[PDB]
Image (spheres, coloured by chain):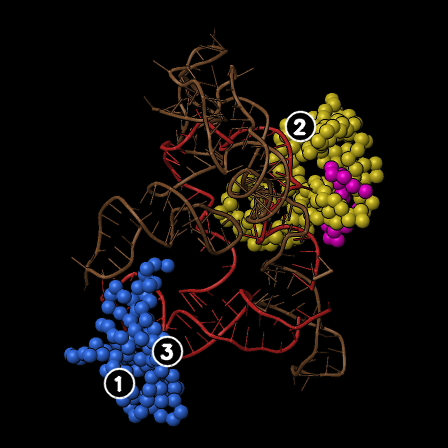
Chain colours: A blue, B yellow, C brown, D red
Amino acid sequence: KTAPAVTLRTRKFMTNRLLSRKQFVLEVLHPGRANVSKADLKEKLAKLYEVKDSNCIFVFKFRTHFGGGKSTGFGLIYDNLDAAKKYEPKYRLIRNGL
Amino acid sequence: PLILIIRNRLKYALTYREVISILMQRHVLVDGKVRTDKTYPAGFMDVISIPKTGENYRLLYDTKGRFRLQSVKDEDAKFKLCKVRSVQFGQKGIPYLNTYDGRTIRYPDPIIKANDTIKIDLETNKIVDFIKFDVGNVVMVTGGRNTGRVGVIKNREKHKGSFETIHVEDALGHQFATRLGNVFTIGKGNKPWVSLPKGK
RNA sequence: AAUCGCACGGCCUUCGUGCCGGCGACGCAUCAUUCAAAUUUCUGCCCUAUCAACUUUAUGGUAGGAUAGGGGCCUACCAUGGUGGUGACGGGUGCGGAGAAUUAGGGUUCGAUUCCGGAGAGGGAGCCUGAGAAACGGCUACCACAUCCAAGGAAG
RNA sequence: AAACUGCGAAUGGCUCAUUAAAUCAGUUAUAGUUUGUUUGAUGGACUCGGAUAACCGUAGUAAUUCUAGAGCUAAUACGUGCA
Protein backbone atom coordinates (compact mmCIF):
# COMPACT_ATOMS: atom_id res chain seq x y z
CA LYS A 1 0.00 0.00 0.00
CA THR A 2 2.25 2.51 1.58
CA ALA A 3 4.03 5.40 0.03
CA PRO A 4 6.98 7.22 -1.03
CA ALA A 5 6.86 8.81 -4.34
CA VAL A 6 4.78 7.97 -7.57
CA THR A 7 2.51 8.85 -10.51
CA LEU A 8 -0.28 8.12 -12.95
CA ARG A 9 -0.32 7.65 -16.65
CA THR A 10 -4.01 8.11 -17.72
CA ARG A 11 -4.51 5.65 -20.49
CA LYS A 12 -7.99 6.29 -21.93
CA PHE A 13 -11.17 6.52 -19.49
CA MET A 14 -15.06 5.77 -20.58
CA THR A 15 -18.90 6.35 -19.40
CA ASN A 16 -22.37 4.79 -19.10
CA ARG A 17 -24.39 8.07 -19.24
CA LEU A 18 -28.08 7.48 -18.27
CA LEU A 19 -26.77 6.53 -14.99
CA SER A 20 -24.12 7.79 -12.84
CA ARG A 21 -20.82 6.66 -14.49
CA LYS A 22 -17.49 8.13 -16.79
CA GLN A 23 -14.45 5.80 -16.20
CA PHE A 24 -11.17 6.70 -14.70
CA VAL A 25 -7.86 5.27 -15.83
CA LEU A 26 -4.16 5.28 -14.83
CA GLU A 27 -1.36 2.96 -14.25
CA VAL A 28 0.36 4.33 -11.05
CA LEU A 29 3.96 4.75 -11.54
CA HIS A 30 7.27 5.15 -9.87
CA PRO A 31 9.07 2.57 -12.12
CA GLY A 32 12.97 2.69 -12.14
CA ARG A 33 13.65 2.17 -8.40
CA ALA A 34 11.00 2.84 -5.82
CA ASN A 35 7.34 3.08 -4.93
CA VAL A 36 3.63 3.73 -5.10
CA SER A 37 2.14 7.26 -3.92
CA LYS A 38 0.09 9.81 -2.12
CA ALA A 39 0.93 13.15 -3.75
CA ASP A 40 0.35 12.58 -7.34
CA LEU A 41 -2.62 10.34 -6.66
CA LYS A 42 -4.16 12.96 -4.43
CA GLU A 43 -3.74 15.67 -7.03
CA LYS A 44 -5.49 13.66 -9.66
CA LEU A 45 -8.24 12.79 -7.11
CA ALA A 46 -8.80 16.33 -5.94
CA LYS A 47 -8.79 17.96 -9.42
CA LEU A 48 -10.97 15.24 -10.41
CA TYR A 49 -13.49 17.47 -8.28
CA GLU A 50 -15.16 20.09 -6.02
CA VAL A 51 -16.43 17.49 -3.41
CA LYS A 52 -17.33 17.38 0.31
CA ASP A 53 -18.08 14.33 2.39
CA SER A 54 -15.73 11.33 2.11
CA ASN A 55 -15.03 12.39 -1.51
CA CYS A 56 -16.84 10.85 -4.49
CA ILE A 57 -13.67 8.76 -4.79
CA PHE A 58 -13.37 5.32 -3.42
CA VAL A 59 -9.65 4.23 -3.64
CA PHE A 60 -8.96 0.66 -2.62
CA LYS A 61 -7.74 -1.71 -5.40
CA PHE A 62 -3.82 -1.58 -4.80
CA ARG A 63 -2.36 -5.01 -5.60
CA THR A 64 1.35 -4.61 -6.90
CA HIS A 65 3.51 -7.37 -5.74
CA PHE A 66 6.17 -8.86 -3.36
CA GLY A 67 7.29 -10.49 -6.61
CA GLY A 68 6.72 -7.59 -9.44
CA GLY A 69 6.21 -3.69 -10.87
CA LYS A 70 2.86 -3.90 -12.37
CA SER A 71 0.30 -2.83 -10.21
CA THR A 72 -1.50 -0.35 -12.07
CA GLY A 73 -3.81 1.42 -9.98
CA PHE A 74 -6.28 3.97 -10.78
CA GLY A 75 -9.40 5.27 -8.41
CA LEU A 76 -13.37 5.56 -8.33
CA ILE A 77 -16.41 8.24 -9.50
CA TYR A 78 -20.71 9.82 -9.08
CA ASP A 79 -19.41 11.59 -11.57
CA ASN A 80 -16.30 13.64 -12.61
CA LEU A 81 -14.88 15.51 -15.55
CA ASP A 82 -11.28 14.37 -15.13
CA ALA A 83 -12.94 10.91 -15.06
CA ALA A 84 -14.57 11.53 -18.41
CA LYS A 85 -11.36 13.14 -19.69
CA LYS A 86 -8.87 10.53 -20.98
CA TYR A 87 -11.86 8.77 -22.70
CA GLU A 88 -15.33 10.62 -22.73
CA PRO A 89 -18.90 8.76 -22.70
CA LYS A 90 -19.26 5.21 -24.24
CA TYR A 91 -21.25 2.47 -22.50
CA ARG A 92 -24.58 4.27 -22.69
CA LEU A 93 -23.30 4.18 -26.26
CA ILE A 94 -22.99 0.41 -26.03
CA ARG A 95 -26.64 0.45 -24.77
CA ASN A 96 -27.84 2.85 -27.61
CA GLY A 97 -27.64 -0.54 -28.71
CA LEU A 98 -25.36 -2.69 -30.90
CA PRO B 1 -26.70 -49.19 -44.83
CA LEU B 2 -24.14 -51.33 -42.94
CA ILE B 3 -25.86 -51.21 -39.61
CA LEU B 4 -29.29 -52.26 -40.86
CA ILE B 5 -27.87 -55.15 -42.84
CA ILE B 6 -25.69 -56.61 -40.02
CA ARG B 7 -28.56 -55.95 -37.75
CA ASN B 8 -30.71 -57.90 -40.40
CA ARG B 9 -28.43 -61.01 -39.89
CA LEU B 10 -29.19 -60.79 -36.12
CA LYS B 11 -33.09 -60.45 -36.03
CA TYR B 12 -33.64 -63.08 -33.26
CA ALA B 13 -33.39 -60.57 -30.38
CA LEU B 14 -31.54 -58.00 -28.29
CA THR B 15 -29.30 -55.37 -29.91
CA TYR B 16 -30.02 -51.98 -31.62
CA ARG B 17 -29.57 -49.53 -28.68
CA GLU B 18 -26.57 -51.95 -27.79
CA VAL B 19 -25.54 -51.80 -31.59
CA ILE B 20 -22.60 -49.65 -31.22
CA SER B 21 -20.58 -52.43 -29.43
CA ILE B 22 -20.60 -54.74 -32.47
CA LEU B 23 -18.91 -52.22 -34.53
CA MET B 24 -16.40 -51.35 -31.67
CA GLN B 25 -15.48 -55.03 -31.39
CA ARG B 26 -13.90 -54.27 -34.77
CA HIS B 27 -15.19 -57.63 -35.96
CA VAL B 28 -16.89 -56.18 -39.08
CA LEU B 29 -15.26 -55.43 -42.40
CA VAL B 30 -16.62 -53.94 -45.59
CA ASP B 31 -14.66 -54.74 -48.74
CA GLY B 32 -11.79 -55.99 -46.60
CA LYS B 33 -11.53 -52.87 -44.42
CA VAL B 34 -12.16 -51.84 -40.82
CA ARG B 35 -15.07 -49.50 -40.22
CA THR B 36 -16.77 -49.27 -36.79
CA ASP B 37 -19.26 -46.66 -37.96
CA LYS B 38 -22.89 -46.25 -36.97
CA THR B 39 -24.10 -43.95 -39.92
CA TYR B 40 -22.17 -46.06 -42.58
CA PRO B 41 -24.02 -47.00 -45.87
CA ALA B 42 -23.53 -50.26 -47.77
CA GLY B 43 -25.07 -51.51 -50.96
CA PHE B 44 -25.20 -54.21 -53.61
CA MET B 45 -22.14 -56.41 -54.11
CA ASP B 46 -20.38 -55.10 -51.04
CA VAL B 47 -18.54 -57.88 -49.24
CA ILE B 48 -19.19 -57.88 -45.42
CA SER B 49 -17.14 -60.00 -43.13
CA ILE B 50 -17.00 -61.43 -39.56
CA PRO B 51 -14.45 -63.09 -37.06
CA LYS B 52 -11.45 -64.72 -36.53
CA THR B 53 -13.24 -68.18 -36.34
CA GLY B 54 -15.44 -66.52 -39.04
CA GLU B 55 -17.22 -66.12 -42.38
CA ASN B 56 -18.00 -63.73 -45.34
CA TYR B 57 -21.35 -62.49 -46.75
CA ARG B 58 -22.33 -60.54 -49.93
CA LEU B 59 -24.94 -57.83 -50.05
CA LEU B 60 -27.59 -58.93 -52.52
CA TYR B 61 -31.26 -58.26 -53.12
CA ASP B 62 -34.08 -60.63 -52.31
CA THR B 63 -36.81 -61.25 -54.97
CA LYS B 64 -38.79 -58.19 -53.82
CA GLY B 65 -35.83 -55.74 -53.72
CA ARG B 66 -34.52 -55.10 -50.16
CA PHE B 67 -30.82 -55.38 -49.51
CA ARG B 68 -29.91 -58.42 -47.48
CA LEU B 69 -26.85 -60.49 -46.63
CA GLN B 70 -26.15 -63.83 -48.23
CA SER B 71 -23.43 -66.22 -47.21
CA VAL B 72 -20.48 -66.01 -49.55
CA LYS B 73 -17.54 -68.26 -50.25
CA ASP B 74 -14.10 -67.08 -49.30
CA GLU B 75 -13.06 -67.55 -52.90
CA ASP B 76 -15.79 -65.26 -54.19
CA ALA B 77 -15.24 -62.91 -51.28
CA LYS B 78 -12.00 -61.83 -52.91
CA PHE B 79 -13.83 -60.24 -55.80
CA LYS B 80 -16.47 -57.59 -56.33
CA LEU B 81 -18.28 -56.33 -59.43
CA CYS B 82 -18.72 -52.64 -59.86
CA LYS B 83 -21.26 -51.25 -62.27
CA VAL B 84 -20.25 -48.14 -64.14
CA ARG B 85 -23.02 -45.80 -63.08
CA SER B 86 -21.78 -42.63 -64.71
CA VAL B 87 -19.01 -41.08 -66.61
CA GLN B 88 -17.59 -37.57 -66.83
CA PHE B 89 -15.72 -37.81 -69.92
CA GLY B 90 -12.54 -37.63 -70.49
CA GLN B 91 -8.66 -37.98 -70.30
CA LYS B 92 -6.34 -39.71 -73.16
CA GLY B 93 -9.03 -42.22 -73.04
CA ILE B 94 -9.78 -41.88 -69.35
CA PRO B 95 -13.35 -41.31 -68.67
CA TYR B 96 -13.79 -40.64 -64.86
CA LEU B 97 -15.85 -43.83 -64.58
CA ASN B 98 -18.04 -43.57 -61.57
CA THR B 99 -19.19 -46.88 -60.13
CA TYR B 100 -22.25 -47.85 -58.08
CA ASP B 101 -20.42 -48.16 -54.77
CA GLY B 102 -19.18 -44.62 -55.14
CA ARG B 103 -15.56 -45.55 -56.31
CA THR B 104 -13.58 -43.42 -58.75
CA ILE B 105 -11.59 -44.74 -61.58
CA ARG B 106 -9.75 -42.54 -63.93
CA TYR B 107 -8.32 -44.24 -66.93
CA PRO B 108 -7.28 -47.50 -68.80
CA ASP B 109 -7.97 -50.83 -68.80
CA PRO B 110 -9.08 -51.50 -72.46
CA ILE B 111 -13.06 -50.19 -73.29
CA ILE B 112 -16.28 -48.47 -71.58
CA LYS B 113 -19.83 -47.27 -71.30
CA ALA B 114 -22.36 -46.91 -68.52
CA ASN B 115 -23.90 -50.23 -67.57
CA ASP B 116 -20.64 -52.05 -68.21
CA THR B 117 -19.24 -53.73 -65.14
CA ILE B 118 -15.76 -53.97 -63.78
CA LYS B 119 -14.51 -57.02 -61.94
CA ILE B 120 -12.21 -55.87 -59.21
CA ASP B 121 -10.25 -57.71 -56.53
CA LEU B 122 -10.16 -56.15 -53.18
CA GLU B 123 -6.67 -55.85 -51.73
CA THR B 124 -4.90 -54.03 -54.57
CA ASN B 125 -7.86 -52.30 -56.21
CA LYS B 126 -7.13 -54.06 -59.38
CA ILE B 127 -9.45 -54.43 -62.33
CA VAL B 128 -9.40 -57.98 -63.63
CA ASP B 129 -12.02 -57.78 -66.33
CA PHE B 130 -14.78 -55.82 -67.90
CA ILE B 131 -18.18 -57.36 -68.38
CA LYS B 132 -19.86 -55.65 -71.27
CA PHE B 133 -23.52 -54.87 -71.39
CA ASP B 134 -24.26 -56.57 -74.66
CA VAL B 135 -26.27 -59.45 -76.00
CA GLY B 136 -25.07 -62.87 -74.99
CA ASN B 137 -23.94 -61.75 -71.56
CA VAL B 138 -25.69 -62.60 -68.30
CA VAL B 139 -27.15 -60.11 -65.87
CA MET B 140 -28.82 -59.95 -62.46
CA VAL B 141 -31.73 -57.61 -61.87
CA THR B 142 -31.33 -55.01 -59.12
CA GLY B 143 -34.85 -53.79 -58.47
CA GLY B 144 -38.59 -54.16 -58.41
CA ARG B 145 -41.16 -56.91 -58.59
CA ASN B 146 -38.90 -58.31 -61.30
CA THR B 147 -35.82 -58.31 -58.62
CA GLY B 148 -33.59 -61.21 -57.73
CA ARG B 149 -33.82 -62.90 -61.23
CA VAL B 150 -30.99 -63.48 -63.76
CA GLY B 151 -31.02 -63.82 -67.51
CA VAL B 152 -29.02 -63.62 -70.70
CA ILE B 153 -29.43 -60.54 -72.81
CA LYS B 154 -31.15 -61.29 -76.08
CA ASN B 155 -31.24 -57.75 -77.39
CA ARG B 156 -31.06 -54.12 -76.33
CA GLU B 157 -33.28 -51.42 -77.68
CA LYS B 158 -32.01 -47.89 -77.86
CA HIS B 159 -34.16 -44.84 -78.29
CA LYS B 160 -33.93 -41.13 -77.93
CA GLY B 161 -32.89 -39.78 -74.58
CA SER B 162 -31.85 -43.09 -73.15
CA PHE B 163 -31.46 -46.72 -73.98
CA GLU B 164 -34.83 -47.82 -72.91
CA THR B 165 -35.07 -51.62 -72.38
CA ILE B 166 -32.90 -54.67 -72.24
CA HIS B 167 -34.51 -57.87 -73.39
CA VAL B 168 -33.68 -61.25 -71.98
CA GLU B 169 -33.94 -64.62 -73.61
CA ASP B 170 -34.47 -66.37 -70.67
CA ALA B 171 -36.06 -67.81 -68.16
CA LEU B 172 -36.82 -71.20 -67.04
CA GLY B 173 -40.32 -70.27 -68.06
CA HIS B 174 -40.38 -67.02 -70.24
CA GLN B 175 -38.98 -63.80 -71.72
CA PHE B 176 -38.90 -60.54 -69.97
CA ALA B 177 -37.35 -57.12 -70.36
CA THR B 178 -36.38 -54.33 -68.04
CA ARG B 179 -34.89 -50.84 -68.30
CA LEU B 180 -31.12 -50.63 -68.31
CA GLY B 181 -30.92 -49.14 -64.85
CA ASN B 182 -32.21 -52.46 -63.48
CA VAL B 183 -29.63 -54.53 -65.29
CA PHE B 184 -26.39 -55.48 -63.51
CA THR B 185 -24.01 -57.56 -65.62
CA ILE B 186 -22.52 -60.61 -63.95
CA GLY B 187 -21.10 -62.86 -66.64
CA LYS B 188 -19.54 -63.18 -70.07
CA GLY B 189 -18.11 -66.11 -71.92
CA ASN B 190 -14.72 -65.43 -70.45
CA LYS B 191 -15.71 -64.75 -66.90
CA PRO B 192 -18.87 -65.48 -64.89
CA TRP B 193 -19.96 -64.75 -61.31
CA VAL B 194 -22.97 -67.06 -61.68
CA SER B 195 -23.24 -70.14 -59.44
CA LEU B 196 -26.33 -69.35 -57.42
CA PRO B 197 -29.59 -71.24 -57.63
CA LYS B 198 -32.92 -70.22 -59.69
CA GLY B 199 -35.50 -68.30 -60.79
CA LYS B 200 -38.72 -67.13 -61.84
C1' A C 1 -1.60 -14.04 -70.62
C1' A C 2 -1.78 -12.90 -65.98
C1' U C 3 0.13 -33.57 -33.97
C1' C C 4 -2.59 -37.50 -30.64
C1' G C 5 -2.55 -43.00 -29.10
C1' C C 6 0.37 -47.90 -29.46
C1' A C 7 4.48 -49.69 -31.50
C1' C C 8 8.69 -52.22 -32.93
C1' G C 9 13.13 -52.44 -36.40
C1' G C 10 17.64 -51.72 -39.50
C1' C C 11 22.15 -48.72 -39.67
C1' C C 12 27.77 -45.49 -37.19
C1' U C 13 25.06 -46.90 -32.94
C1' U C 14 24.90 -48.54 -24.53
C1' C C 15 20.66 -45.33 -23.15
C1' G C 16 23.53 -41.40 -27.33
C1' U C 17 21.78 -39.05 -32.60
C1' G C 18 20.76 -38.35 -38.40
C1' C C 19 16.48 -39.21 -42.28
C1' C C 20 12.87 -42.54 -43.21
C1' G C 21 9.61 -46.03 -41.88
C1' G C 22 2.66 -50.84 -39.55
C1' C C 23 -2.00 -49.20 -38.09
C1' G C 24 -5.83 -46.96 -35.82
C1' A C 25 -9.14 -41.26 -36.05
C1' C C 26 -7.30 -36.33 -37.85
C1' G C 27 -7.34 -32.59 -41.34
C1' C C 28 -8.12 -28.77 -45.33
C1' A C 29 -8.80 -27.98 -50.45
C1' U C 30 -14.68 -29.73 -55.31
C1' C C 31 -10.33 -31.87 -58.54
C1' A C 32 -15.66 -36.39 -61.84
C1' U C 33 -19.07 -37.58 -57.51
C1' U C 34 -21.92 -41.36 -53.20
C1' C C 35 -26.40 -41.16 -48.60
C1' A C 36 -28.25 -36.69 -47.85
C1' A C 37 -30.09 -30.65 -51.76
C1' A C 38 -32.27 -26.81 -54.51
C1' U C 39 -34.32 -24.18 -58.95
C1' U C 40 -37.42 -25.05 -63.61
C1' U C 41 -41.17 -27.64 -67.10
C1' C C 42 -45.71 -30.88 -70.73
C1' U C 43 -50.33 -31.98 -66.73
C1' G C 44 -54.36 -31.52 -63.02
C1' C C 45 -55.69 -29.42 -58.38
C1' C C 46 -62.88 -25.55 -54.77
C1' C C 47 -67.05 -22.08 -56.03
C1' U C 48 -68.57 -17.72 -57.82
C1' A C 49 -68.91 -14.44 -64.83
C1' U C 50 -74.91 -10.28 -60.06
C1' C C 51 -65.93 -10.87 -61.70
C1' A C 52 -65.81 -9.82 -68.21
C1' A C 53 -61.86 -7.28 -70.53
C1' C C 54 -56.47 -7.61 -67.63
C1' U C 55 -51.55 -5.82 -66.47
C1' U C 56 -47.23 -1.08 -66.46
C1' U C 57 -40.19 -4.58 -65.18
C1' A C 58 -45.38 -6.25 -66.38
C1' U C 59 -44.77 -8.03 -70.97
C1' G C 60 -40.85 -8.88 -74.95
C1' G C 61 -35.31 -8.32 -77.68
C1' U C 62 -30.35 -7.29 -76.38
C1' A C 63 -26.02 -6.12 -72.80
C1' G C 64 -24.32 -6.14 -67.66
C1' G C 65 -24.63 -6.99 -62.60
C1' A C 66 -26.21 -10.80 -58.88
C1' U C 67 -26.34 -15.73 -57.09
C1' A C 68 -24.13 -22.06 -55.25
C1' G C 69 -26.56 -22.17 -59.94
C1' G C 70 -31.80 -20.29 -64.05
C1' G C 71 -33.49 -15.73 -64.97
C1' G C 72 -37.73 -8.50 -65.67
C1' C C 73 -34.88 -11.85 -59.66
C1' C C 74 -32.40 -6.76 -59.80
C1' U C 75 -30.80 -2.88 -63.40
C1' A C 76 -29.80 0.20 -68.31
C1' C C 77 -31.41 0.61 -73.73
C1' C C 78 -34.47 -0.69 -77.56
C1' A C 79 -39.34 -2.94 -78.93
C1' U C 80 -44.95 -1.76 -76.93
C1' G C 81 -46.47 -5.70 -75.59
C1' G C 82 -48.27 -10.74 -73.55
C1' U C 83 -53.44 -12.86 -71.81
C1' G C 84 -58.88 -14.07 -71.75
C1' G C 85 -66.34 -16.66 -74.71
C1' U C 86 -61.49 -23.63 -73.90
C1' G C 87 -63.32 -18.50 -68.06
C1' A C 88 -57.08 -14.92 -68.19
C1' C C 89 -57.23 -10.48 -64.16
C1' G C 90 -60.41 -10.54 -59.82
C1' G C 91 -63.79 -11.99 -55.19
C1' G C 92 -65.34 -15.36 -51.55
C1' U C 93 -64.02 -20.17 -49.43
C1' G C 94 -67.71 -22.60 -41.35
C1' C C 95 -52.95 -26.68 -46.28
C1' G C 96 -52.16 -30.03 -51.04
C1' G C 97 -51.20 -35.15 -51.76
C1' A C 98 -50.90 -40.29 -49.46
C1' G C 99 -55.50 -41.00 -47.77
C1' A C 100 -60.65 -41.31 -44.63
C1' A C 101 -66.23 -42.28 -44.55
C1' U C 102 -70.26 -44.19 -47.97
C1' U C 103 -72.54 -46.80 -51.49
C1' A C 104 -73.70 -53.29 -55.08
C1' G C 105 -71.32 -50.24 -58.60
C1' G C 106 -71.32 -44.56 -59.66
C1' G C 107 -70.35 -40.81 -57.91
C1' U C 108 -70.97 -37.87 -53.69
C1' U C 109 -68.36 -36.35 -49.42
C1' C C 110 -63.79 -35.37 -46.92
C1' G C 111 -58.70 -33.57 -47.17
C1' A C 112 -57.22 -33.07 -41.01
C1' U C 113 -54.35 -34.59 -36.21
C1' U C 114 -50.65 -39.45 -38.54
C1' C C 115 -47.07 -40.61 -43.37
C1' C C 116 -45.11 -36.95 -47.23
C1' G C 117 -43.95 -31.98 -49.16
C1' G C 118 -44.66 -26.59 -47.97
C1' A C 119 -45.29 -22.69 -44.62
C1' G C 120 -44.69 -20.02 -39.33
C1' A C 121 -43.62 -19.51 -34.42
C1' G C 122 -47.13 -12.28 -30.88
C1' G C 123 -47.24 -9.06 -36.10
C1' G C 124 -43.49 -7.62 -39.97
C1' A C 125 -38.64 -6.64 -42.53
C1' G C 126 -33.40 -7.48 -42.32
C1' C C 127 -28.59 -9.87 -40.72
C1' C C 128 -24.50 -12.35 -38.37
C1' U C 129 -22.90 -17.13 -37.39
C1' G C 130 -22.49 -21.85 -39.48
C1' A C 131 -21.52 -26.76 -44.98
C1' G C 132 -26.73 -25.89 -44.41
C1' A C 133 -31.13 -20.97 -40.89
C1' A C 134 -33.43 -16.15 -43.67
C1' A C 135 -33.69 -19.66 -37.28
C1' C C 136 -39.88 -21.48 -31.41
C1' G C 137 -35.15 -22.98 -27.39
C1' G C 138 -29.80 -16.36 -31.56
C1' C C 139 -29.64 -11.38 -32.68
C1' U C 140 -31.34 -6.59 -34.36
C1' A C 141 -35.37 -3.77 -33.54
C1' C C 142 -40.31 -0.73 -34.74
C1' C C 143 -45.02 -1.98 -32.81
C1' A C 144 -48.51 -5.32 -29.47
C1' C C 145 -48.85 -7.40 -24.71
C1' A C 146 -47.64 -9.62 -19.72
C1' U C 147 -42.64 -8.85 -16.21
C1' C C 148 -38.32 -7.26 -12.90
C1' C C 149 -36.94 -2.89 -10.35
C1' A C 150 -32.23 -0.76 -4.61
C1' A C 151 -38.10 1.75 -9.91
C1' G C 152 -30.85 3.61 -13.42
C1' G C 153 -31.81 0.05 -16.64
C1' A C 154 -32.72 -4.89 -17.85
C1' A C 155 -36.60 -8.47 -19.31
C1' G C 156 -39.62 -12.35 -22.44
C1' A D 1 -13.13 -31.90 -14.65
C1' A D 2 -14.29 -25.97 -15.79
C1' A D 3 -13.43 -22.43 -20.47
C1' C D 4 -11.26 -21.95 -25.93
C1' U D 5 -11.32 -24.54 -30.90
C1' G D 6 -13.67 -28.70 -33.94
C1' C D 7 -18.94 -31.65 -34.80
C1' G D 8 -24.04 -30.10 -32.95
C1' A D 9 -27.95 -26.72 -31.11
C1' A D 10 -31.14 -25.71 -38.57
C1' U D 11 -32.34 -32.53 -37.48
C1' G D 12 -36.35 -33.16 -34.38
C1' G D 13 -41.12 -31.61 -32.30
C1' C D 14 -46.35 -29.29 -33.01
C1' U D 15 -50.12 -26.14 -35.56
C1' C D 16 -52.95 -25.39 -40.69
C1' A D 17 -53.22 -19.14 -39.49
C1' U D 18 -51.46 -18.15 -44.46
C1' U D 19 -53.25 -21.15 -48.27
C1' A D 20 -56.29 -22.66 -55.69
C1' A D 21 -50.27 -21.70 -56.12
C1' A D 22 -45.11 -24.98 -60.56
C1' U D 23 -48.03 -24.66 -53.45
C1' C D 24 -48.20 -30.09 -54.03
C1' A D 25 -48.61 -34.38 -56.67
C1' G D 26 -46.55 -37.53 -60.92
C1' U D 27 -42.95 -37.22 -64.98
C1' U D 28 -38.65 -34.97 -66.69
C1' A D 29 -34.84 -31.21 -66.99
C1' U D 30 -30.39 -29.75 -64.57
C1' A D 31 -22.53 -29.64 -67.94
C1' G D 32 -28.00 -24.30 -65.91
C1' U D 33 -25.94 -26.12 -60.08
C1' U D 34 -24.61 -26.90 -54.97
C1' U D 35 -23.09 -31.91 -51.30
C1' G D 36 -19.02 -29.61 -46.02
C1' U D 37 -19.04 -34.03 -42.37
C1' U D 38 -19.19 -39.49 -44.17
C1' U D 39 -19.05 -43.99 -47.18
C1' G D 40 -15.38 -43.44 -51.23
C1' A D 41 -11.75 -40.82 -54.42
C1' U D 42 -7.41 -37.39 -55.49
C1' G D 43 -2.85 -34.50 -52.94
C1' G D 44 0.62 -34.51 -49.22
C1' A D 45 7.51 -37.41 -38.61
C1' C D 46 12.98 -30.40 -39.95
C1' U D 47 13.62 -26.17 -36.51
C1' C D 48 9.71 -23.00 -34.09
C1' G D 49 7.15 -18.67 -31.71
C1' G D 50 2.97 -15.86 -30.85
C1' A D 51 -1.91 -14.46 -26.62
C1' U D 52 -5.76 -16.42 -24.31
C1' A D 53 -10.06 -18.53 -20.71
C1' A D 54 -10.67 -21.17 -16.40
C1' C D 55 -7.82 -19.40 -11.73
C1' C D 56 -7.14 -14.60 -9.68
C1' G D 57 -7.87 -9.59 -7.57
C1' U D 58 -11.16 -5.59 -7.35
C1' A D 59 -15.35 -3.31 -9.83
C1' G D 60 -19.57 -0.01 -12.62
C1' U D 61 -24.88 1.46 -13.81
C1' A D 62 -25.16 -1.91 -9.16
C1' A D 63 -29.57 -6.04 -5.19
C1' U D 64 -29.26 -6.07 -10.47
C1' U D 65 -29.17 -8.41 -15.16
C1' C D 66 -24.68 -8.15 -17.44
C1' U D 67 -18.87 -7.29 -18.63
C1' A D 68 -14.76 -4.96 -17.83
C1' G D 69 -9.21 -1.88 -15.17
C1' A D 70 -6.73 -6.30 -14.15
C1' G D 71 -2.17 -10.68 -12.64
C1' C D 72 -1.32 -15.80 -14.91
C1' U D 73 -1.43 -19.44 -18.76
C1' A D 74 -2.24 -23.87 -23.05
C1' A D 75 -3.48 -24.22 -28.54
C1' U D 76 -3.95 -30.20 -35.36
C1' A D 77 -8.47 -22.85 -33.68
C1' C D 78 -3.48 -18.71 -36.05
C1' G D 79 1.08 -17.28 -38.73
C1' U D 80 5.26 -19.05 -41.36
C1' G D 81 9.18 -20.42 -43.98
C1' C D 82 8.04 -25.38 -48.31
C1' A D 83 9.08 -29.96 -54.72
Which residue is at a point 25% across and 74% down the rendered structure image?
A80
Nearer to us in this view, B181 or D71? D71
Are the residues under badges 2 and 3 in a single subunit? no
The residue that appears at 22% across and 79% down in the rendered structure is A49
Tell me the quarter of the picture where residue B132 sits. top right
Type of amino acid at the residue the image marks with label 3: Arg
Horizontal side of C37 relative to B168 (left or right) equals left
Please, what secondary structure does the residue beneath circle 3 have? loop
Determine the main secondary structure of the stretch shown in magenta. Answer: loop
Please state if A33 lies on the left or on the right of A61 as rendered: right
Amino acid of disc 1: Glu
Instruction: Give the spatial CA distance, label 2 vs label 3.
Output: 83 Å
| Helix, strand or loop at mark 2 | loop
Q: How far is disc 3 from disc 1 in space, using C-alphas?
A: 17 Å
Does residue B18 appear in this view?
A: yes
Q: Is residue C16 above or below residue D27?
A: below
Point out the stretch of residues depicted in magenta: B111-128
Q: Magenta segment: does it hold B124?
A: yes
Q: CA distance from mark 2 to mark 1?
A: 98 Å
